[PDB]
């Protein structure tokens, strides 16, 4: 098993304040305002109004 | 300053003036208050736990 081919793929990610290009298979939800509500904006998870 | 010492002479004032001087004294400082979670954590339930 040591001397056997092993295909390798390395993924490198950039989490910058720039428009998102690759996203997970999550479903967007409607906007709720003026309520203390958990939110997830393009990976930014937080609690706020 | 030149001060002359004499065994038989004394200097006495012949007039006077009224001097008003100011003295500034701090008496109190701003009263501050802090919150445990809103500072250390914010609104994160996991951080509060």
Image (tube, coloured by chain):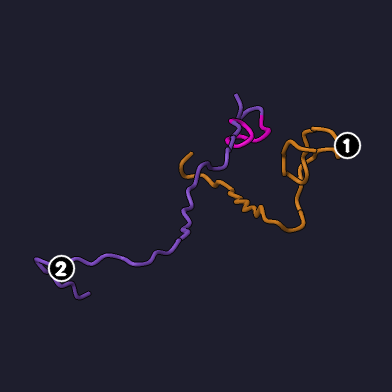
Residue located at (75% from left, 51% from top): A22
Q: Chain of mark 1?
A: A
Label of residue A7 in the image? none
Considering the numbered disc 2 on the image, is that residue within a helix, a strand or a loop? loop
Considering the numbered disc 1 on the image, is that residue within a helix, a strand or a loop? loop
Mark 2: give few (<14), some (14-19) or many (20+) Cα within 10 Å. Answer: few
- The residue closer to the viewer here, A5 or B21, is B21
Q: Quadrant of the C terminus of chain A?
A: top right
Q: CA distance from mark 1 to mark 2?
A: 95 Å
Which residue was labeled with disc 1? Answer: A32
Q: Is residue B10 left or right of residue A24?
A: left
> Given the current orientation, which residue lies at the most extreme right position?
A30
Percent x, y of residue A1: 49, 38
The quarter holding residue A47 reads top right
Which residue was labeled with disc 2? Answer: B9
- The residue closer to the viewer here, B12 or B23, is B12
Is A33 covered by the magenta stretch?
no
Q: Is residue B43 left or right of residue A7?
A: right
> Given the current orientation, which residue lies at the most extreme top position?
B49
Q: Is residue B23 left or right of residue A36?
A: left
Is B37 covered by the magenta stretch?
yes
**Colour orange, chain:** A
The magenta stretch spans which residues? Answer: B36-44
Percent x, y of residue A2: 46, 41
The colour chain B appears in is purple
Residue located at (11% from left, 66% from top): B8
Mark 1: give few (<14), some (14-19) or many (20+) Cα within 10 Å. Answer: few
């Amino acid at each position: 098993v040591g001397h056997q081919p092993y295909r390798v793929v390395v993924l490198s990610f950039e989490l910058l304040n720039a428009p998102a290009t690759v996203c997970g298979p999550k479903l967007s939800t409607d906007l709720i305002k003026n309520q203390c509500v958990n939110f997830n904006f393009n990976g930014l998870t937080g609690t706020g109004v | 300053s030149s001060i002359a010492y004499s065994n038989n002479t004394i200097a006495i004032p012949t007039n006077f003036s009224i001097s008003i001087t100011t003295e500034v004294m701090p008496v109190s400082m701003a009263k501050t208050s802090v919150d445990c979670n809103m500072y250390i954590c914010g609104d994160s339930t996991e951080c509060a736990n």
